Image (cartoon, rainbow over all chains, first blue to last red; front, top):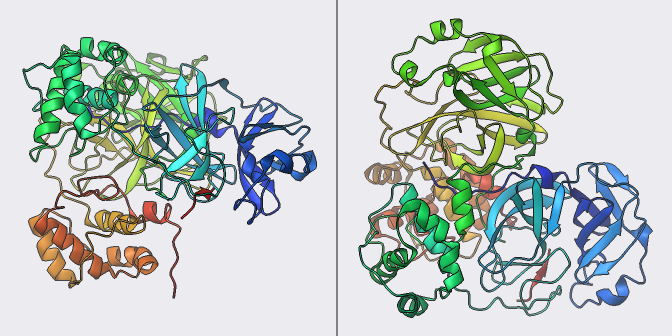
Length: 306
Length: 306
Length: 6
């Protein structure tokens, strides 16, 4: 029993964090094989962020200007490049601690663990979800750029996020491992705005499944609501609508508990309309939408990673 | 910006995880140097857990009966002794991955990371605090006994907890890395009862400072209090008495924000007597006590204007 | 208040 917000084992990823410096401005990078990925905004100084042009700044700079460090042992940059917002450095040695890896772009409502780094050294790890507005509610201070968001499937680490910038509302923004930002954001210190976020309904239902598995059942009403009928009520409360694919995603969770997916939506509907009534679900008095049905299974089935 | 719970990077700990199987029982063991420490009840079955004489049970078991797995290669048990509630297994091989480590015994209120494990492999990592009743609100399933709780201060791993059992309420009981349990619990099939929990006042005041530092300032009032006046109120809402040492620790956050510890205490007296009037703090609708001032300081880069 | 490059 017990249900926590869990981060993935950060072992394999810690082994890829390198420190990329450039005289005044330093940040973190990922060292997989003989490639070093680090946000392109490292080729800047305190004045270049105000209004940048990475297109030509990369051109006027070369291999020697980069200062890579694997803790203490500096690395030789033998090739520069710019795939969108990330900088592809080339090193004279493949990372001996490189895990089996994938590069994956995720959808909103999907989760990953973030290994927070400063000067190529990991300081902490936490579970995050791509909000439906493509921002993350992260915990990053200046110098946390480079820090990755990943997921572990079997023995293979799947990289999904690179930290680039913060927004004025305290929330965070970054690109995939190819440099394509998540959302309509650019890597500049310009007027940027997160926009209306919604609640990840598929993750809220999956969260209540973990509460049913862990004993909390008071909210389990014996009524039903059609899929569209639920989407009628849910949308009033700023909750992402439920697709039929979402129902298929909750299928295994439903089968493993006995409670139907359509029944669970009716238990959620009255939960939203009437409120908590003092009581808490899983120790919280708010609905947690940061648990995909997969994170619910991996926690409540002792799913380990090699 | 941002304020979130973070486990330490579990890297170092993952390199110390081995699976200890005796008879039908399998749990986890920490592999430090040529000793593998694991909970002592791995040598018992259900009928043995009823009223055990561990001294005899260990007599009936030999080195050959302890199948210690370190992934591919199985390690060789070459001697075994029992220290309090832990079994220490001597192995023919020093752990090449043994980090610079320590066996600390934390106090109620102190926080640590848990590398949850099954069969010597990690499932996930999460922060959890030592409750005042000596339990920990963790996420544990069968086979999780042997997993460890730790802290990391520059290359040194301070081990404070080894997982043992789950109590009726869902909370968890365990021991320091020397075998001595946290609290009045014992590894026996007696009817143990988890004591009545109390709130960690100093960690709620620290979380209130963290919230001030992230914009949240609605709960602030034009009022202040005295220490024992606050402790009189604390008693009613089952809050742990705030001691002068706690006031000392809060100083840093109190200076960063110009809000006196007692000026802040008076806002908590008000939150407890008036309710949060349907408003969240740092995205939570309840008072969080699992965030120490040390965690907040580690995540807030504000300035004291002096 | 503009965005912040970390």
